[PDB]
Length: 52
Length: 52
Image (cartoon, rainbow over all chains, first blue to last red; front, side, top):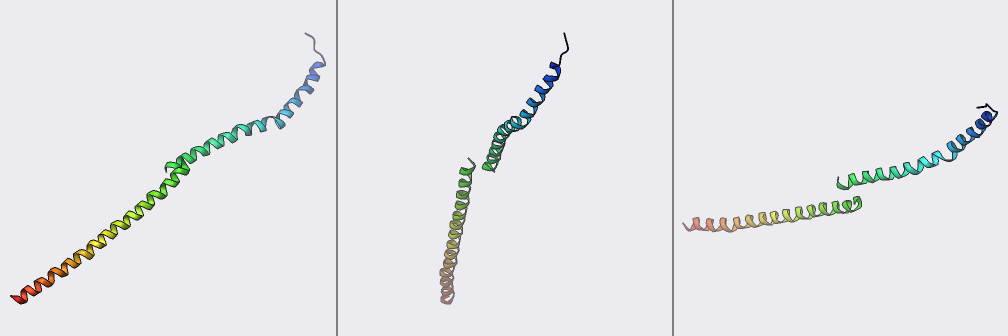
């Protein structure tokens, strides 16, 4: 339809949501999974030595 | 399970130890038994020769 300065404003609206995510959402959520995965892996290590 | 198996591994070692000792004990007993039967027989045969 019509180009509008809205195209510029949406660039402002966009970037911030990237940074707030990058800092305050993604790493904290990756840790939540990976720590549980580590616990299950060391569980397997214990299972190994348990019979060894 | 790994804690329980560590607790199990001491018992098998301990029983191998004690039974090794009872076995060597009985074998030493038998040596001290046969070496005595040997004396009891040897002296009788000595006396039999001198009586010959």
